[PDB]
Length: 557
Ligand SMILES: [Zn+2]
Image 1 (tube, protein in one colour):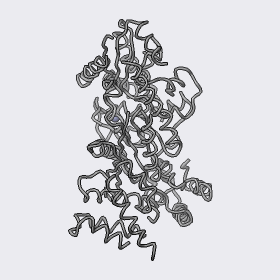
Image 2 (cartoon, protein in one colour):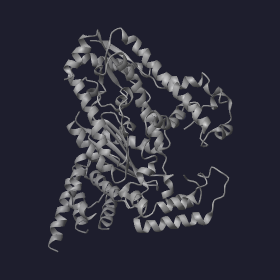
Image 3 (cartoon, protein in one colour):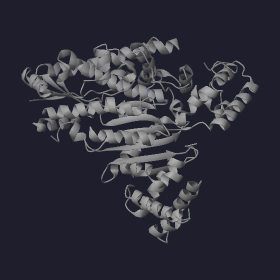
C-alpha cells in the first residue's frame, strides 16, 4: 500500500529528499547518575526528534516521512492525535536520523524551522526547570551565556537532494559531513561556576550537594514534566527496583512482610527508597538520607536489621545485581539509509523496524524490567539478573523474522556501582568486544562483582539455545566443584591438552554414569563451536566463564 503513498509525495510536490540527524546521542545518555537520568536523557532525545518530525508532519503529512515509520509511533498517537495512550509512551522509540520527502521550496525553511523548534522547546524546558529547582542569582540564572549552552548543545544537521539509491548514498555522506563541522554531573560549564563562584560555594547552593549544568537540570525536571503532560512516570524508579524482581523476591517480600517493614520504617523516620529493602543500608549509612538535624532512634535501626535478616532466612537473600542490556543491529548502517537497495522497499524496511521496536521488543520486556529505548534495531533495558539472557535471546529471534543479524552486550553489575561507568562498560562489550568478531552476531556477557572482578564471555546466540536443552544445565555444588576446577586448568592451559583435560574433568564430576559422562563431553564440545574464540583454550575459557557467571551464587542467590 506504500507505493501509492510515495507516488503522491514524489509526484504531487516538486520532490527533494530531506534528512535529519541530532548529533549528541551516546555522550548525552552516558552522562547520567541514577536510572531515572538514563531514561530521562534518552527519552528527551526522542522528544527532540519528535519536534523535528512534528514540523515535517505539520506542513505536509505523515506518509511523507520514510524513516522512521510514524504509524504506531506512541509520541504521535498521544501527542499529535491526542490518543489516550497507555504506558507505551514511557519508552523512547524514535531514533535520531530521519528521511522525509519534502517540497523543493520548503527545504530551506524546514531546516531553520527545525533548528528553532528544538531550541525553543529546550529553552522552554530550562525555564520550567529553573522554576522547579527554586521550588525545591535566580534572576541571573537565565543569562544569555547560559541560554547558549541550551541552544548550542544538540546539533541538528539537515541536508537535501533533488529526486536512485545513489542519491540516498550521496545524501548520507554529504549529511555526515555537516555534523562535526557544526563541571557538573561533564565538560559543560555549571549553571553558576561559569560567571564567578568558588567550588565550595557552588556545591552548597545545589539541591543534592551536586552542582548541575543547564542540560542536566533538564534531565532532572523531565520526569515531572512528563508526568504532567502525559499521565504517568517510569514504573521501576531505581536500578534497585528492577534488581529486586529476581525470582519475585520483592513481591514475596511485600506479602509475608512489607507492611511491617513500612511500619518499622515509619517509626525510625519518614522515608515516605528501595535501598532500604537491604539490611546493609540501615547499618551502613542512613546519614545521607537524614536531610534534617532530627534524632534517629537506634533500637529501631538495630531491630529493622533483625527483621530483614530473619526475613532473608525464610525468603532468601535480596538480589543485589542487575543487568544492563544494550542491543544494536549488524551491518545495517547502509540498510536503514537505503544504499543496499528510494522504492517502497525502503519504507517496508522502515515499517519492519518500527514494528519490531515498538511492539515486539515491548512484548518481550513486558513489565519484567525497564525498557528504556528501542529505535528500530537498537535497545537499552535494565533487567533483573534472571531475565537478562532470556530477554536478549527472545529479542534476537524476533529481529530475525522482521535486516538480518544483531549483537548484544549484557552487563551484570552490583547495585551500588556508578551507573556512568556501568553504562560505559556495557557499551564497550557490545562495540569493542561483541561487534569485533568476524561473523559479528554475538552476545558479549560481562559480570563485574563488587570485588572488582570482571568476567567477560563472548558467545554465539545458538549457545543459549543448546544450553537450555542441555543435560549439563540439569545438574548445575557438583557444578561449583566442576566449573571452578575447569577454569583453574584453563587459567593458563592444561599442558596435558584441551581434549584430554575435559575427559578427565567430565570423568571426575552406575549404568547411567557412563552414558551421562559421555553425553556431557558431547554437549561441552558442541557448546564450544558457539563460543566466539580463536582456539580451544579461548573457547573453553569462554564457555566456562559463561558457566561461571550464570551460576555465581552472589549474583544468583
Ligand atoms: Zn551536566
